[PDB]
Image (tube, rainbow over all chains, first blue to last red; front, side, top):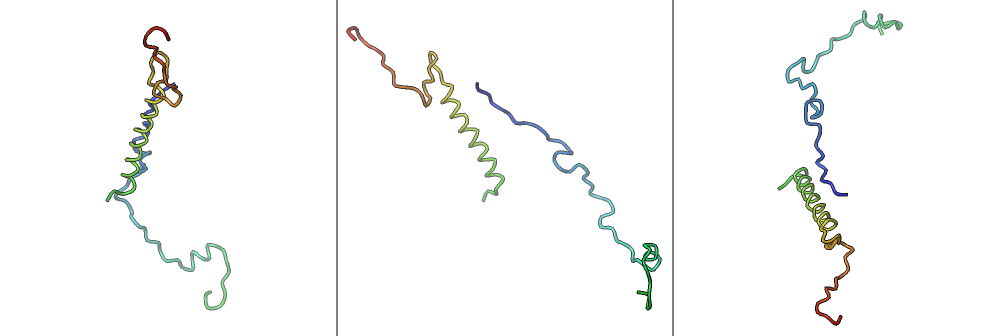
Amino acid sequence: GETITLNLSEISVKTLGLDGFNVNGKGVTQNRSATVTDVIAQGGTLQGDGT
Amino acid sequence: SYSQEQLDSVQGEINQRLADIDRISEQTDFNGVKVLSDSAKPLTLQVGAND
């Protein structure tokens, strides 16, 4: 009727939360400015003054 | 000076000690008597003849 539960589990990568810990890499990527080609590729409409 | 997590570990040890105290209470047995429990009436120990 008596026990001493240990409650031991889950010490590893993928449970300490890192799971992908990547000190290097692209960091913060910089997007490129859009232009008329991209917008007309999205298929909308143009009008006066290029709007 | 102790941050919250060290207090959490301290409280974990407090809970372990309190649970052990309760275990001692409910498991200290003598001739099938939970002597140091919450249900242990005082004993008689008849000493001498002529009760």
